[PDB]
Length: 48
Length: 48
Image (cartoon, rainbow over all chains, first blue to last red; front, top):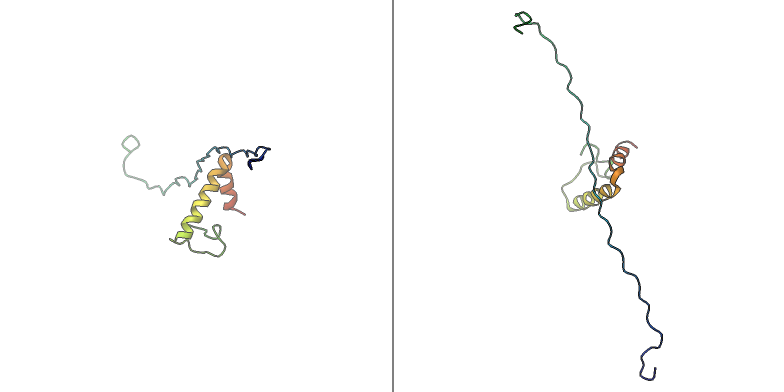
């Protein structure tokens, strides 16, 4: 203008949106229990 | 811990250092950003 102020208005850039935070549960896989060696005892079946 | 080659191919011994901590942070951040496929990404990096 006569005073130095601009006629055409300014551009308003869009701000960035807040992102959505993500989490996860990674999982493991260990081996199972393997059977030991069997020993024969001295007692009968109802006692053992 | 077991295969530090999968962390970096030059490391071969996972250190107690600040760059190892920072790279652990970014690794955990990428894996948690993977979301629902995080365990699949981890077990696919377990293999090649």
